[PDB]
Image 1: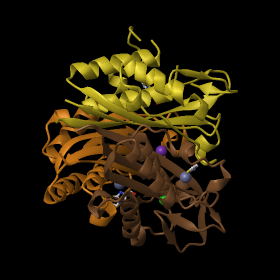
Image 2: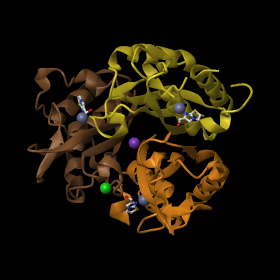
Image 3: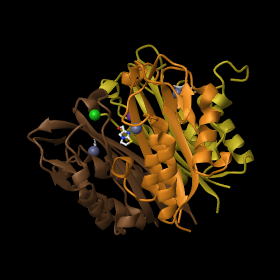
Image 4: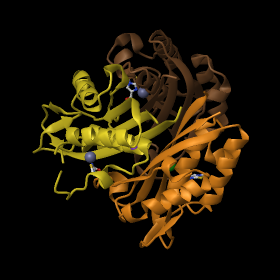
Length: 148
Length: 153
Length: 158
Ligand SMILES: OCc1cn2ccsc2n1
Ligand SMILES: OCc1cn2ccsc2n1
Ligand SMILES: OCc1cn2ccsc2n1
Ligand SMILES: [Cl-]
Ligand SMILES: [K+]
Ligand SMILES: [Zn+2]
Ligand SMILES: [Zn+2]
Ligand SMILES: [Zn+2]
């Protein structure tokens, strides 16, 4: 069977006067992520990981973030691949993310037409190190397994 | 078959006053991590990720009365993975540290992790990098670990 | 069905007076990557992912930055030797995915050429090789153009 892996990375700046939206979840917070889209860093990383596993290039070449994630899933099926699983990590010093994880996972599973058991989201701080540790941005990493 | 992938990430600050333990191995150095075993946490997270069981924070709470060092957590991680129905196929990882030289300690880390995961030694890999003097990592202010894991249901 | 995954990371400083070589592509630029070999950050990251999947250690060990024979070494030759060792250990490569993170220059015009180089070196079709390019959204040493980072993932089978 023809399995493929993909990995994705994203980061966005935390700025005043934007809502904080991660994995489709709006999180109460003084700042939000800056981007041309809704800057959903988690969804962007998953999107890149899915495009990478299908060898379809990247999000910058192809393109709210859930609509884009749905379009990615479409283009991935279009190339003849089915999604097996997604795993990810959010790196954010603040705010606390644990209470929103299940919602993110629910959002992603719905967007990718996957059961909850094939979608995972993990949260981490950066132990006060670098721009992430100073709360200047939020990073997401993703890994996706697909099969043709 | 029903294969799944997971990925893991971890970082800790590097300062005088603590031992340096990476992958179960105490390494002589003028600094240490605030056991704070970056490599084992990353691998733990990667395993929980592949299993879709959340993350290290949800399983082993920083307050929970039952928690032990990072090898014990790794061992526990692996039993939870097994019970969800998953066999571990392989782990690969990278440690990024500007100093000390990590190459000498890799075989011991691979041995500890393989022991802890009940894996054949040739299914466990650890790699070493510096940050080429860039950022907090390159200034020796912290050490990062990265992990990938493949499992099967 | 004996599948294995590997992952890779690399970063090099971006300095004046060096060629900029990423994915085997020499990119016109006033700066280039600093290292012992040609400093091709993307190929090193993929090489690490491949050694990692086969559990063969790492590129720093197979191709040491302290060994003079690798001075100015062609990282495509290094990737091809890696692939040869991975094959020798019994693995076939199934796919590679990767990311390059750089403030500058624009990498989109060069991505297809990089993909082509990697596919050639690994004896893979283009449809099993992927290279993604981003910026770091102006953040950190990458945002300041002090270095270029690459990340990689590889799937192999014994
Ligand atoms: O680098 C942040 C970023 C750029 N980009 C383009 C499409 S989605 C997206 N995220
Ligand atoms: O980011 C450092 C860190 C946080 N955390 C929570 C459980 S194990 C662990 N390492
Ligand atoms: O850390 C940058 C680096 C060192 N090294 C040794 C062989 S390939 C390579 N890239
Ligand atoms: Cl940037
Ligand atoms: K990083
Ligand atoms: Zn983004
Ligand atoms: Zn940790
Ligand atoms: Zn390198």
